Length: 166
Ligand SMILES: Cc1cc2nc3c(=O)[nH]c(=O)nc-3n(C[C@H](O)[C@H](O)[C@H](O)CO)c2cc1C
Ligand SMILES: CCCCCCCCCO[C@@H]1O[C@H](CO)[C@@H](O)[C@H](O)[C@H]1O
Image (cartoon, rainbow, N blue to C red; front, side):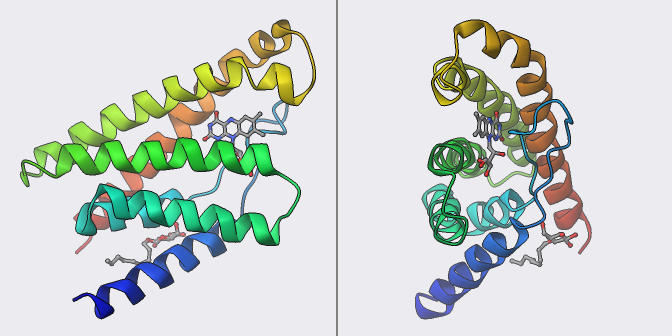
């Protein structure tokens, strides 16, 4: 209820900023791809309060996380760009047919989109970030694909066993 909800968002984003400190590289080769489950707070916020609010959370989350981990602008900007895209799409699908069907149809789609958005993004970033030629990206390609497919897929199914578990 306005003031009651502003605080709810504020502590959930500050909750996600916390969870972002258990980030681990999962892939030993790809030390740049690091998994954190902080996209599960925003996915919950996006379902209750709307797609724009969910992106606001991951936006402020990564800003705070960047203020505390000052030294990864492009990486954090990548996580913010991919993160905002994951929740806003999942929020939008859920948000015209309250039917629980749109909950998973949005997560299946959002997981696929954010995965595709990551490959296209890294295509002109992994060359630029490592100041390398385009072939390095292609060495990393199946790991970038498997990562964001697993990261957002896990976040999709974990948020579902949160709604289930009630
Ligand atoms: C080159 C680079 C590529 C990244 N690619 C992805 C990605 O494909 N999917 C994802 O979820 N996060 C990705 N990240 C997010 C990363 O785990 C997070 O931003 C770390 O905080 C990097 O500092 C990427 C980060 C960098 C630096
Ligand atoms: C609007 C109310 C929503 C409920 C919020 C309670 C906490 C967040 C939901 O799940 C939790 O998230 C953590 C971080 O990702 C996980 O580590 C943890 O295992 C899991 O239990």
